[PDB]
Image (cartoon, coloured by chain):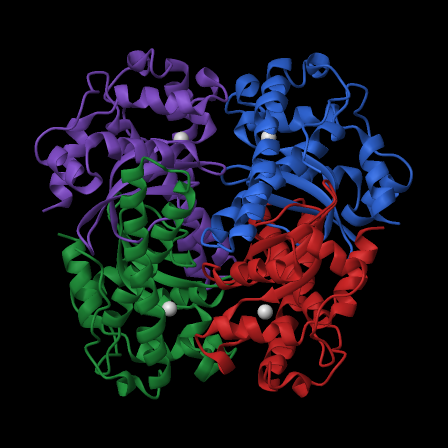
Chain colours: A purple, B green, C blue, D red
Amino acid sequence: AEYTLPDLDWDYGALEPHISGQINELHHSKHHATYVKGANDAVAKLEEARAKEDHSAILLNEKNLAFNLAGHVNHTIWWKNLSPNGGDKPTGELAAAIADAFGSFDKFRAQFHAAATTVQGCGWAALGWDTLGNKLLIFQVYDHQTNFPLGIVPLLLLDMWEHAFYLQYKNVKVDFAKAFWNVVNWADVQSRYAAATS
Amino acid sequence: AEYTLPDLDWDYGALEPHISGQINELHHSKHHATYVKGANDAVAKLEEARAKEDHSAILLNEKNLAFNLAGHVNHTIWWKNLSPNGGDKPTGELAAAIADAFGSFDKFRAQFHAAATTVQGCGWAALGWDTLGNKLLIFQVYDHQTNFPLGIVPLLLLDMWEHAFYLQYKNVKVDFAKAFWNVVNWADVQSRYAAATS
Amino acid sequence: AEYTLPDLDWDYGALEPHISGQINELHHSKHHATYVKGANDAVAKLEEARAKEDHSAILLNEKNLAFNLAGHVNHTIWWKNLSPNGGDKPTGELAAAIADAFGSFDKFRAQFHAAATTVQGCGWAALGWDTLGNKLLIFQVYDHQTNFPLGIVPLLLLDMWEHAFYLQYKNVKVDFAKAFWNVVNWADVQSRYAAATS
Amino acid sequence: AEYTLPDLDWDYGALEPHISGQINELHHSKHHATYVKGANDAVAKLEEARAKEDHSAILLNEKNLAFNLAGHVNHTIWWKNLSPNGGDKPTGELAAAIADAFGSFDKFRAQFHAAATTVQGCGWAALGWDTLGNKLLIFQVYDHQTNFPLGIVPLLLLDMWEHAFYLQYKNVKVDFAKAFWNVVNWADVQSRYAAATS
Ligand SMILES: [Fe+3]
Ligand SMILES: [Fe+3]
Ligand SMILES: [Fe+3]
Ligand SMILES: [Fe+3]
């Protein structure tokens, strides 16, 4: 069936002071909603293109599909990676994993921070699981659909687009990137890692 | 552990006339080998960057990692998607799936062909499974790591980079794209779809 | 010599209500300043790379140079394309040009608006002069350095990055894009066109 | 008027052994011809889009325009940057310039070589003149239209796409990149630099 805008497991304001409610609100209700509509439209244009046997606009239809489905997939996971009762550090299996792959939770965290704060333009920082080599790796995503291999399982993401913090942090994206660690919902990531490693 | 250059399940020449042995040879032994080395180097630079607590070159390290791990992941699957005893059409579950999502195997195939022949520069055509919406979709990949959402499971790919056919088809990439249907190994794709839908 | 942050020909607030002073301020003093420093650093890294005969990081040095020199070049022109005493329509040579190349100033303006409001991620809308074919064309720039040919002379640009309007228009980028027409400084564009056509 | 496929100032074979005639032939007659047609088509789609007051496909029309006009602009200059009677080193003003901006012709040349041999996918190496800062700089172009600022004047380019050497050098692009120095037509570059610095 169609793609749909998910419900947050919390109130927009629940993340203050780390993330203003106004942000979460426009983010969810305007930005994410827009991707979901775009993903569905893209899918429909394809059907219509397929029926008329007219792929003249294949390049645009395929690019619209990737961009919008990618924004949807990303925000879908972002809402879950966040939580008012989170913060602290990972635990158990996930933590031993992380320390074994990035030397220590602190070192993982320095890299991830680096990756999110150096994007040239808009993008995200994401931790994922590589199934080919069975390794935990950090990628620097450009926009929403660029810079990472096919089949990588996403575990944790940090939205670096300006719409994600300009209202509250203005140009100080380094601050926003630090504040994030207070709202990460480790029960989710841990969960995702468990499923990915199965 | 490290990433490694896989072995082909066939002899380089096994695909003639559809795909010259000389191609398969340079492709596997030179191009793919290069990605695998690059993927391992990228991974190491990260470790070294992590130890020195020096992420000054984060952008390059992350981009090298995505590009090379992506070429590796892609060729890894390409070798399996090919077979001297393939061709024909998909069967069973996969075929009903394909006809249900693209109207008919013929229509799927017209779209896929369109997607591979219109790349602007180098890229690939790929069929993948979207887990968010549980749908079969075709994407037009740019280079190796661009244009598609995170977490998409790759099922079938068609290498559109010039190195994949210039020696034999020269600039006639439309011909190469047609010849491909004779060597697709449907037992593999079908297999992948089965695992993806589980 | 080095690259330097130019002075605005006006006060930050001079564009209200169309463009808030707070924006112009962070935009000029934080964002643009950052590109200028980055452009100079990029240039230096190259010298140092050239002296040591060590181009191991060529890809990053070249990408840093393009990104930062491009942001600098872009904002440099943006400040000039804006003016408190502007608005209205182009005049003389430029206007006949524009109507002859886009049918009418109104049609040019519909296209330009379309180009700026559909960027996927961050970018700009720019009108430039193609010297090869001697034509006026509109391009949709991605980020700061992507999507247009070498040697194109830039005449007018509209910054579509979120930092350019999020504080005041929030996610309503369509509004910001309309408000812009009130502050365009046609004496500048006209001037640039004159020099480009010489 | 329309865009047109230029005539070479030489015979396809004139560059052997450095560059096979077969290459120059398919390159000029197939590849470049394709960009020119594409550039004209893109321009027409815009007119038609403008008349119907229907910019639904703005993103594709603008991307087709940039890609094809960019390939055209690039090959246009490549044919001129090449010559059977070239090679050697730059002379006069251009040479003092080059040594002053890259330390020495040898150092310029090491950088340029680095830039062309590390492209991730398809692209070019280009020397251009920055008018904002009045400096000679080397850029690493991705595809044909990406990675460099607006208004940069192109002086010399080296086509790194696989179609530019696969037939003769196969995957050994490092060799092709070396062979190029024997056919550079310095009278052209010098000329371009003169006009750019005016
Ligand atoms: Fe976002
Ligand atoms: Fe390949
Ligand atoms: Fe800006
Ligand atoms: Fe070429």
Residue B166 can be seen in this image: yes
Q: Residue D160 placed where, x, y %?
A: 54, 66
Q: Residue at x 8, y 31 (%)?
A: A92
Q: Nearer the viewer, residue B78 or A171?
A: A171
Q: Residue furthest right?
A: C92
Residue D107: which quarter of the image? bottom right
Count the marks: 0
Q: Residue at x 26, y 86 (%)?
A: B14
Q: Residue C190 placed where, x, y %?
A: 84, 37
Q: Residue B147 placed where, x, y %?
A: 41, 51
Residue B20 can be seen in this image: no
Q: In the image, ligand 4 is in what quadrant?
A: bottom right
Q: Residue at x 78, y 55 (%)?
A: C131
Residue C191: which quarter of the image? top right
Residue B22: which quarter of the image? bottom left
The answer to whether B191 appears left or right of B179 in the picture is left
Q: Residue at x 67, y 18 (%)?
A: C18
Q: Residue C26 placed where, x, y %?
A: 58, 19
Q: Nearer the viewer, residue B149 or C172?
A: B149
Q: Residue furthest front?
A: C52
The answer to whether D192 appears left or right of D125 in the picture is right
Q: Nearer the viewer, residue B18 or A139?
A: A139
